[PDB]
Length: 156
Length: 39
Ligand SMILES: O=C(Nc1ccc2c(c1)CNC2)c1cccc2nc(C(F)(F)F)[nH]c12
Image (cartoon, rainbow over all chains, first blue to last red; front, top):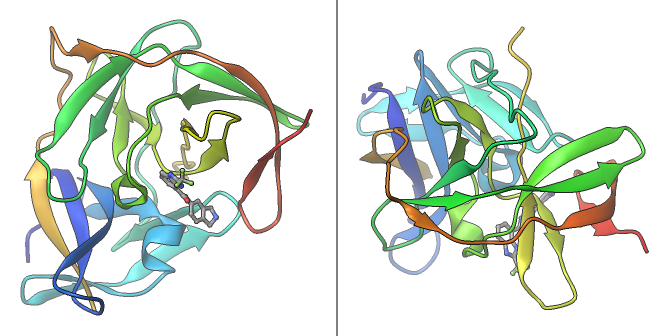
C-alpha cells in the first residue's frame, strides 16, 4: 500500500484497542524499524503486505521489502534532532547534543531524551535531514530516565 | 497483526525545542541486543 518516504507509526490490534508498539522510517521502498518492535513479524500497510528482508537481534534492527538503506552517521560534534513520534501524540522534532556510550568495541552516540517505549524506531536526524540512526535501544540511568544509543545499520 | 500509519515527513526543523543532556556512559552490549551499565 503506502510506500511514500517518511516516518510511520507501528500499531497492533492484538492488545486492548489499537496500541502503538513502535515507529519506523520508509526510505527508497524499504521500511526500517527496531527488532524489538516487530520481533521480525510481517507488517500490513492498508491492503498491502511488508515482509522482513534483513534483521539482527544484537544490532536491534530490521528492514522490510529490501536491504537497510540508511547510512548517514553522527559527525561526533553537532547537535541532532530526535523526530519523536510518541503514542497518541503528534510527530515532534527535539534538538539535543548527544552524549557517548563507551563500549569494548568503540563509541556510539547517545541521546538523553526520555520517551515511552512505544516511541522505539523514531529517527535521529542531522542538519541535512538525513537519518543517522533510530531511538529505542539503550540503558536506564540512576535517575530512572532512559538514555538511548543512536543505532545505525549498514548499507550493503 | 501489525500495521503501519504515516506520521509525517523527515525534515530538520529550525527553531525546534532544544533539551537533553550529553552523558558519557560506560556500557556493555550482550548477545540479546541489551545494553547495561558498567561501573
Ligand atoms: O525497553 C526499551 N527498549 C528495548 C526493549 C526491548 C529490547 C531492546 C530495547 C533491545 N533488546 C530487546 C525502551 C525503548 C524506549 C524507551 C524506553 N524507556 C524504557 C524504560 F521504561 F525502561 F525506561 N525502556 C525503553
